Amino acid sequence: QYPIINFTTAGATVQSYTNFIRAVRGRLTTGADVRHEIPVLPNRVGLPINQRFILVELSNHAELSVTLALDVTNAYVVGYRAGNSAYFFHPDNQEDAEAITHLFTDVQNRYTFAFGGNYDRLEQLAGNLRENIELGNGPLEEAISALYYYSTGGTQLPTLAISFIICIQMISEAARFQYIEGEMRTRIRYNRRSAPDPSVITLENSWGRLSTAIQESNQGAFASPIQLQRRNGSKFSVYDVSILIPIIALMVYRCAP
Ligand SMILES: Nc1nc(O)c(CCCc2ccc(C(=O)O)cc2)c(=O)[nH]1
Image 1 (cartoon, rainbow, N blue to C red):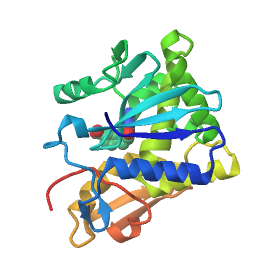
Image 2: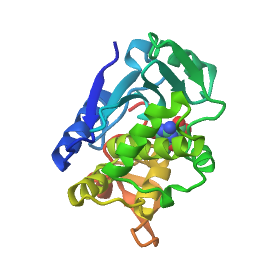
Image 3: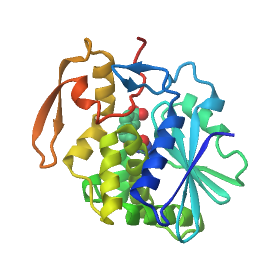
C-alpha cells in the first residue's frame, strides 16, 4: 500500500500540525537530491507506480474521515476517498490517467470529474478566488466534512471546490513552503480564520518558476530576478536562492544536476 499520514482537526495544535506537515514532507521525498540546500521531489520520468503517491488521512472531531491522494513528484492533490466512493480530477494526460488507476483500488465507486484540479478551474466552480476563501482549522474541519458528504448528494459543487482549495493550501502548499506552513500555524495558534494575503498567493503561483530558477541558478544567483509580493500587495525582486532557504521547502524536479 501507499504511505499514509494522518491528521485530525479535533484538538489540533501548532505542534500536531507541524508534526503532520513534517511527516508529509518526509514521505513526499527521501531528500537525497538537494540543490543549493533545497530538497527536490522525485523525477516523473523514471518513477514507478508503487512509489508515486502518498495518502493523507484527514479526520474531524465529528469523527468522519477522508483520504487525499498526493502526487509525489509535485505534492499535487489528484483525488480523494470518502467511504465507498473515490473521486479524481480530470488528468492532464494518459500517463497520469493510467497512474491514478492504482489508487483506492478497493472502493466500490470510482469517478473522474469533467474538470481538472488547477486553482483557476476550482475558483470558477467555487465562485470565489483564493483571496476570499478563509483558511484555518475551522475551514479545514468544514472542508473535510464537505468532502465526506459529497457522495451522498449533501454537498453542492461550489462548496466542494471551496473545500478542495482549502485542503490544497493547508497541505500541499504548506508542505511546499515553510512560509505557508507558518501561516497556517499562526491561525491554528490564535484560533483564527482568514483568507491568504498576497505573499501567500504569489508564492503559490510562482512555485514552478522558483523551482526552475533555483535549479538553473549560478551557485544560487538567479539568471534573472523573480518578482514576488509582500503582505500588503507590493512587488519586490528576489535575486538569489539564499533569501528563500527559510521560505521554500521542496521543488519540482526540473532537470539533472
Ligand atoms: N489540485 C491541486 N493541487 C495542487 O497541489 C495545486 C498547487 C498549485 C501550484 C501548481 C504548480 C504546477 C502545477 C502543474 O502544472 O502540475 C500544478 C499546481 C493546484 O493548483 N491544484
